[PDB]
Figure 1 (cartoon, rainbow, N blue to C red):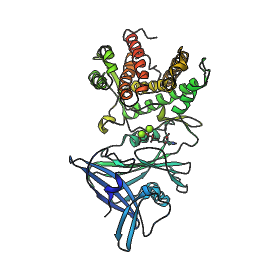
Figure 2 (cartoon, helix red, strand yellow):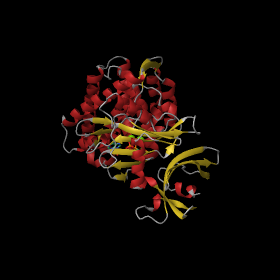
Figure 3 (tube, protein in one colour):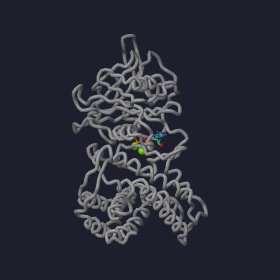
Figure 4 (cartoon, rainbow, N blue to C red):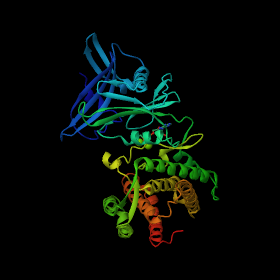
Length: 451
Ligand SMILES: Nc1ncnc2c1ncn2[C@@H]1O[C@H](COP(=O)(O)OP(=O)(O)CP(=O)(O)O)[C@@H](O)[C@H]1O
Ligand SMILES: [Mg+2]
Ligand SMILES: [Mg+2]
């Protein structure tokens, strides 16, 4: 036995928030080696809720040097005497062992590992745990592959694994290729599946779209917007449309009414967080209600798309992180949606990339608004390029259904406003400006005045 509860509450991936833990106990312990245990740990709260975490424990008969305090779980008596329990994901040999189980498509008790057909795993490469802030734990093997081990685990089909598999197996080149994964059952053999981790090809020497965009939007004296990042935005549009096309073919398309009631509920909630919104709520609602009964085509989509979710390798843009929007339940995250909502996500991201500069400057540094003008011009140029690149692949310009597109942009801006009002008041002018602009964009498109 180990004092799991005392250890887990200090971990950055632990989501207990401000809650009292009743118990933290292993639901399932699966030996991998004589000194390596896979553990499904159930944390029970006072309201009776249970949240399950995945832990891999490396046992040692004496203090091992390389483990930090955060990787030290506890101590316990075993058959040969005292043992120390370490978080095995920080052990190179243990991480390699997991990768080997994936490589072999091994089954260990109720744990099912699978290597994607034809995939090669870098079993020789040095494993190093990612230092990047996240809710899971990732081990990078050399420059070749990333093993992501999920911390909080839940029942059902994992959309990140699911959609990456579809895309990779269809030969889509705009993903970091899924190389393998592993899972178990929720309540023993014969019950709901539970995804545990994934292995993906590591995109070495890549840049995040957000970093490239902000660099472009910060270039001094760039009053005449350049063509280089527009070229990149066009290529990114190609990539997003390509991903959408593969997903549409594999997982189908259908039609639904535009979700007026859903976006209205989000508006009502947002207006409680951002009082600034009440002055615009009537106008937003009118635009949404004009779409009542509008049929929209939906399909499986990325679901949380922005410039932080795309990587530029030396050869291509890749889309990563298909888990869906962080706050939604799994069934909702696997629902089809409009591809235009993904497009809207990128357009919002361009807006923030350009205007972050302005909210960080003092008023006196842009008294005549010329940097603001440049930001607007940069967003317009790159948004147009992105949409054109999308159109080149889709064979249909997202701006054609401009009313639906603008409504999704508006819904995102309303959500952003509520967020900034709560967490970052100085950023609130960004979505508020967007709302006024998009209100006009949407009004124009509803009258079919858009180009
Ligand atoms: N295949 C790959 N090759 C190279 N870098 C990758 C990669 N997959 C992810 N990354 C990088 O690793 C980091 C983590 O990416 P990820 O999409 O998991 O962030 P995230 O913020 O969504 C974590 P969480 O969802 O838990 O909050 C990012 O900096 C991302 O650019
Ligand atoms: Mg991400
Ligand atoms: Mg993520």
